[PDB]
Image: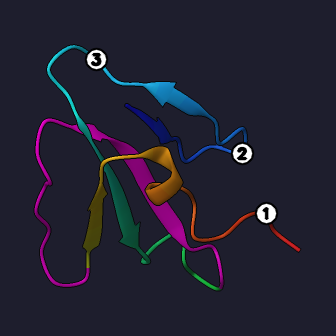
Amino acid sequence: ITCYKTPIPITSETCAPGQNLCYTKTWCDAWCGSRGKVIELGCAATCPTVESYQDIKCCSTDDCNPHPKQKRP
């Protein structure tokens, strides 16, 4: 399985041994001072959990774990 990273060069790469899912961390605070929305992508053996202000989305493929925001205008 592969997933998309967060950085500009959002690319698809295979996970480490034992993993099988990808996670999308959606949040906004310091860096979101205006419109700098941040999102942490990665991999995990199982769908991870979050709190209130923070959100997450688990998928079993990069096509489902990309960046909700392509590139800045």
Circle 3: residue type:
Ala
Q: Earlier in the sequence, mark 3 or mark 2?
A: 2
Residue visible at 21% across and 13% down in the picture: 17
Estimate the x, y position of residue 26 in percent, counting from the top left.
Answer: 39, 70
As measured in the structure, the alpha-carbon distance from the residue carrying label 1 to the one carrying label 3 is 27 Å
Q: Which residue is mark 3?
A: 16
In the picture, residue 35 is in which quadrant? Answer: bottom right
Front position in the image: 4 or 52: 4
Residue visible at 54% across and 77% down in the picture: 32
Q: Which residue is mark 1?
A: 71
Tell me if residue 8 comes above or below residue 64 in the rendering.
Answer: above
Q: Which residue is mark 2?
A: 8
Q: Earlier in the sequence, mark 1 or mark 3?
A: 3
> Is 29 inside the magenta-drawn segment?
no
Mark 3 touches mark 2? (CB < 8 Å): no
Side of 72 where 36 appears, left or right: left
Q: Dot 3: what SS?
A: loop
